[PDB]
Amino acid sequence: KVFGRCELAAAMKRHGLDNYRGYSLGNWVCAAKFESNFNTQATNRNTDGSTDYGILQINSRWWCNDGRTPGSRNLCNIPCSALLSSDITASVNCAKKIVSDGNGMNAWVAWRNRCKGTDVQAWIRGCRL
Image 1 (spheres, rainbow, N blue to C red):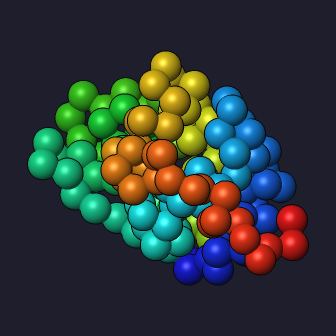
Image 2 (image 1 turned 30 degrees about the horizontal axis):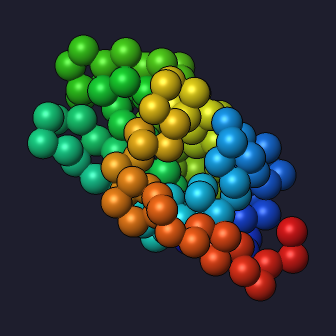
């Protein structure tokens, strides 16, 4: 599913991401924009043999199982395919674990490089939330 911006903002908000670990909703929309362009089906292989999945490009070395990443930990206890669903529940649940792991949203290198320090509230402008 390719979400609209406001459509994703509402979904993330429904699932409890607005202000989760102190990150306002704009941060999460901005991260999803630059990770996946709001596409739940997005996949990207990494140099180390892992792959990133879904709207928030969650990685198969630590968080989900894809059956081809040796020494996968599967900390979210999910197959990586669950992160590609039109239903973002599994991605949100896993994202909440990741952002709690100690480095906040710095875990998403795309957020660090294109969101952090910017006016992230711009990403929820216009939306009925």
